[PDB]
């Protein structure tokens, strides 16, 4: 519907970039993912930054059972991150974990960028990634991660610290969720 | 996006009806509208049950300035509710006031039902009201309320207490917001 909340969240996100506080966030860990999430949803979602205690789904696809989150989250964390493919593989798992009640996609995309920034010196130019193509690649990722790999690989940038490049990407990241 | 939060809110709405707690929500008042909202969004929205202190919009349409909410809310609450037309006019004002950050549509639709129940012993068969027709009528409502008045008048029921009917109704209400 109107998604008024998300308008406010987008502003928190922008604030996160503009203030330089994003450099302060721990990278590649679930703590770091929680930090991102808290920043984006604090004051909006009661569970901002909190691991869910309920099960969630898209269609007939259940995300990781909250029963196992304590086990699988550290296991994802421990995955290697030495190249592009490994990092995308780690991202695909973290998305399957989908550890929050809402806002997994936009928090985890930032998380991914930080991981690519740290290890590869790259980020994803989300605004060059069409929404339908992104969603369909994500939907296929649990079974075949080739689509999402190819799609992210086509659109890396070395322009890793430029505030407006980053803000354009976050704007698109929120557009993926329906905010136009 | 996935709207996991909304699925969780749907279960809370169902529970509100099924448990019979709905029978002691105060009818036709701001406090009552807040009770509804609190109940649907508690533990989901940080702001569950609270009047917003920010401005919100759809397109270039701003809902009532949060600067005036303290003044217009009591004025809306004072509006007559003796017949169908009055109750709908009251509802239309209440939607324009849009006093919460998010979840105005679902809370206020329930609020409408309770008013119609108290006053005319009817409820709206939401599941028989197409979503495009509903959205178009609401969009036109600030300027001309005939569309919404006509649409609602055609899908009223005397069966105000059947919880199957009520659940079908609330499921459709959530569907209006994009929950599928
Ligand atoms: Zn709204
Ligand atoms: Zn999701």
Image: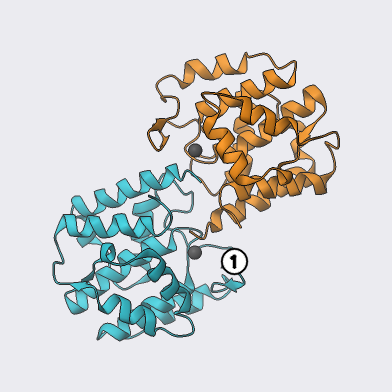
Chain colours: A cyan, B orange
Q: Is residue A11 left or right of residue B145?
A: left
Decide: is A46 above or below B72: below
Q: Point out residue A45 in the picture as x, y percentages from the top left corner.
A: 46, 49
Q: Name which residue lies at 45% across and 32% down.
A: B52
Q: Is residue B19 left or right of residue B88?
A: right
Q: Is residue A88 left or right of residue B103?
A: left
Q: Nearer the viewer, residue B10 or B171?
A: B171
- How many tags in the picture? 1
Q: Point out residue A112 in the picture as x, y percentages from the top left corner.
A: 31, 71
Q: Is residue B177 left or right of residue A118?
A: right
Q: Secondary structure at mark 1?
A: loop
Q: Nearer the viewer, residue A172 or B156?
A: B156
Q: Is residue B54 visible?
A: no
Q: Is residue A28 visible?
A: yes
Q: Point out residue A97 in the picture as x, y percentages from the top left corner.
A: 48, 73
Decide: is B71 above or below B32: above
Where is mark 1, residue-wise?
A: A55
Q: Name which residue lies at 75% across and 49% down.
A: B168
Task: Mark 1: give few (<14), some (14-19) or many (20+) Cα within 10 Å.
Answer: some
Q: Name which residue lies at 26% across and 50% down.
A: A14
**Residue B121 falls in image quadrant:** top right
Q: Nearer the viewer, residue B59 or B107?
A: B59
Q: Name which residue lies at 48% across and 19% down.
A: B70
């Amino acid at each position: 519907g109107h998604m008024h909340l998300d308008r406010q969240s987008l502003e928190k996100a922008k604030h996160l970039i503009q203030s330089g506080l994003i450099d302060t966030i721990e990278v590649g860990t679930i703590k770091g993912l929680q930090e991102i999430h808290r920043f984006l949803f604090e004051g909006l979602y009661e569970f901002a930054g909190k691991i869910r205690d309920k099960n969630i789904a898209k269609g007939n696809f259940r995300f990781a059972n909250c029963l196992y989150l304590d086990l699988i989250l550290p296991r994802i964390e421990s995955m290697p991150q030495n190249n592009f493919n490994q990092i995308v593989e780690k991202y695909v798992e973290m998305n399957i974990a989908h550890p929050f009640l809402e806002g997994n996609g936009r928090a985890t995309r930032i998380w991914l960028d930080l991981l690519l920034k740290k290890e590869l010196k790259k980020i994803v130019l989300w605004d060059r990634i069409d929404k339908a193509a992104y969603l369909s690649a994500m939907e296929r990722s649990p079974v075949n991660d080739l689509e999402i790999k190819t799609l992210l690989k086509k659109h890396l940038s070395s322009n890793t610290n430029d505030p407006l490049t980053l803000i354009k990407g976050i704007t698109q990241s929120y557009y993926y969720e329906g905010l136009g």
